[PDB]
Every structure is written in C-alpha cells, then in structure tokens.
Image 1 (cartoon, rainbow, N blue to C red):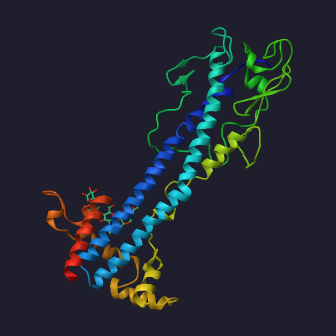
Image 2 (image 1 turned 120 degrees about the horizontal axis):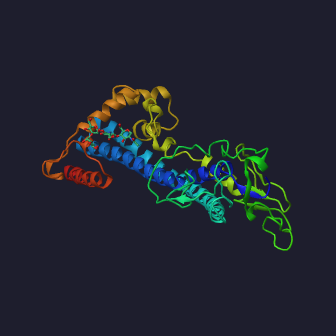
Image 3 (image 1 turned 135 degrees about the vertical axis):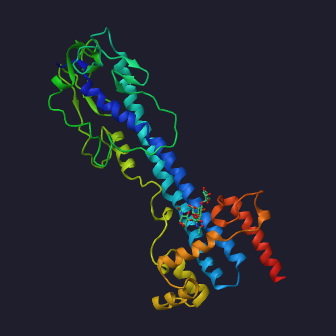
Length: 359
Ligand SMILES: *[C@@H]1O[C@H](CO)[C@@H](O[C@@H]2O[C@H](CO)[C@@H](O[C@@H]3O[C@H](CO)[C@@H](O)[C@H](O[C@H]4O[C@H](CO)[C@@H](O)[C@H](O)[C@@H]4O)[C@@H]3O)[C@H](O)[C@H]2NC(C)=O)[C@H](O)[C@H]1NC(C)=O
C-alpha cells in the first residue's frame, strides 16, 4: 500500500549495485598495475635484444636484434604514452563516478535501515513486508550490503549488475504500491504528505527524489515511482545523471588490452617500427617497395614471417651474459633475467665493452 515501508524487492537491487560499484576501484588499480607491468615486460624484451646486439655486434644476427630491440622499445614507449593520455583518465573517471554513485546509494539505504519503530514497522522490510531487517556484518536481511567502501586490493571484477545496457535489476515497476511498498509498515520516507510522510504541518512543496534521482517520492498519498535504468542512453542534466555517468565511464573501459600492451603476430614487415627502420638505416631511402623491405629482412632473419622473428628471439633468450654480472649461482641466460633496472645496467656494461673494442 502507498506510504508504507519498502519491501526487499525495492532495496535489494540497490544493494546489488552498491556491492558491484565497490569493486570498480579494485578494477582500476588492477588495470593501472597491469598496464605498468606490460610496459615493463616490453622493456625487458627490448633490453635483452639490445644486450644481444652489443655482445654479437657487427653481424647479421646483431642487426636483426637491433630491429627487435627497436620494436619492443617502441611498444614500451607507446604503452607509457597510452597510460598517460588515455588509461589514467578512463580509470580515475570510472573509480570516481562509481564511488560517488555508491555513496549516494549507501547514504539512502543507511537512512532506510535506521528509520524504524519496531520489529514489524519501519522503512526497510523483508521480502514479505513482515519484519524490519537488521544489519549483521556485511549483510542486511541476508542480502550482501556492506554500505561501506571496502579496502582497495587489485581485482578484475565481472560486470553483472551494471553492464553495457545499464543497471539490469533496476527495471520498470508497474505496481509499486504492491511490489515495493509493504501493507502496514509505517515509514515517513515513503511520501511527502504530512499525515504519513515527511510533511509536518502540510505537504512538502514538491515531489522529492532520492538515491541520486532513482526514486520519486510524491507529496501526495501515492506510491513511489522509479526510473527504469536498464536501457540507458547518454544524456546530460538528467535527474538521475550520476547513474548515467557511472554507466558511461564503465562502458568506456578497455583494460590494459589495447594494441600498445599486446604483442604483434603479423609478418615482420608489418611489425611496429620495422619498415621505417629498414628504410632509414638499411636501404637509406624513403618510400620503399614492399619487395625491397622483404628482401632486406631475409638478410637478417632468413625470412620475413613471424616464425623467423621467433627464431631470432630464441637466440636472444638463450644468450648468456658474463658470470660476474649476476649473483653467485644465479642464471646468466638473458631469457632467465627480468627487471628493467637489472637489465639496464647489464646493457651499460656491454656498451662500455663496445667502446673498448673501438678504442
Ligand atoms: C612479448 O613477447 C616477447 C617475446 O616472447 C616477450 O618476451 C619474452 O618474455 C618471456 C617471459 O615471459 C621470456 O621467456 C623465457 O624463456 C626461457 C626459455 O624457455 C625461460 O627459462 C624463462 O623462464 C625463466 O625465467 C623467468 C624470468 O624471465 C622466470 O620468471 C621463470 O620462473 C623461469 O625461471 C622465460 O619463460 C623471453 O626470454 C622473452 N623474450 C625476449 C626476446 O626477451 C614479452 O614479455 C611479451 N610482452 C608482453 C607484454 O607480454
């Protein structure tokens, strides 16, 4: 009945959204760390190839490794630029819009939870509208509903309650007086009229919206109405705008999975940086033919397909460095070394050796 406390079918879908929004900061931290990690892996491969070239310098194998080193250093460069230009804003915006909306929802739900007079009369009722619910740890009436922002650990969340189309559980409600409102539980947050609702001497001067514009509390003796939020469209200045902002920011997320962060399986000529380097440093002519690039490449890779690129990478990975450059009993093959700073100083050692050979 109108002007009565809210049954579980009303507030459980809000709990579900709040719990899922709680994971958006975790996903943002995961993605920012994953981007940095992938950049670091690209840089390690660039450094191994560079070290191999110095060790084997002046050979066709070394020139192949220079091409490989250039490729992976450009991947690392481009991932850092994308982290600056795109990923940082995407992940901060998702974190902020999700956390802001969660705060709007949780403040409303916490008010419902506390506004009660007895075990059978209050604003937050169970599924049958018989008993007011209580919070026990991170649950309310048996529903996960912490009403707090959890400690932020990296995690990959699975979009369930907020997806590509909108908030799946926040559907059009045709019969709120019977499906949202209890039969007898009293709740002055259920209307703006003075007899049973928020008005004191008279009715409130207008309808009131709560939960960032989701629910509309009329100032007459009538049931609430809700915005359907499951088939959203991009808009500006809506009463429920924070729902749209979080949905839009979440839909834009790519993770650390755009092309800068992934390896390329194309033929060698099409791999990042390869054609420009062949043209500028080997052919020494701009606007070259494809046949010429492929012909140059066979000199150094014995072919021009991904298989010949992998073969050079295996030679790079198997190359040992000088024993004294690693700790006692530690591995010396480049493929068994990782960490940018560790490989950077090994490259510097071999560049000094290269200088001493020219001396
Ligand atoms: C894009 O692709 C490149 C090329 O594949 C890739 O660089 C490669 O990274 C792997 C590591 O993921 C290196 O593979 C090594 O292979 C040897 C021989 O089988 C293994 O022994 C290695 O494992 C030992 O060493 C690891 C440290 O590196 C330890 O963590 C591990 O426990 C083992 O003790 C390892 O599998 C390979 O050498 C490089 N290749 C080159 C040319 O550097 C790069 O990481 C990819 N980029 C992204 C973002 O994924």
